[PDB]
Length: 89
Image 1 (spheres, one colour):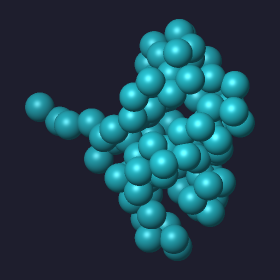
Image 2 (cartoon, rainbow, N blue to C red):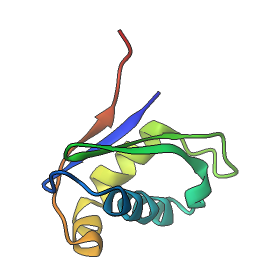
Image 3 (tube, rainbow, N blue to C red):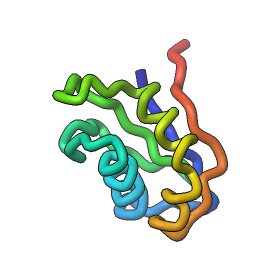
């Protein structure tokens, strides 16, 4: 299951997307090493959460981003415009 966060930065630079992911990881007390395959596509950063000691999943990541959007925006200096989880065709 791939998670994503769409921002108001475009193109969102690989480093900015990485810092945003480490921001959310800090909120969940998971190491950023639990975030695999981190990518930026256009305005979005996407990532997979691998099995970790906090039992945190991709949905937990989504929920934590929603629940802390304001803190995350102030931390990161950008706007979060959508969060969710991807689907395969």
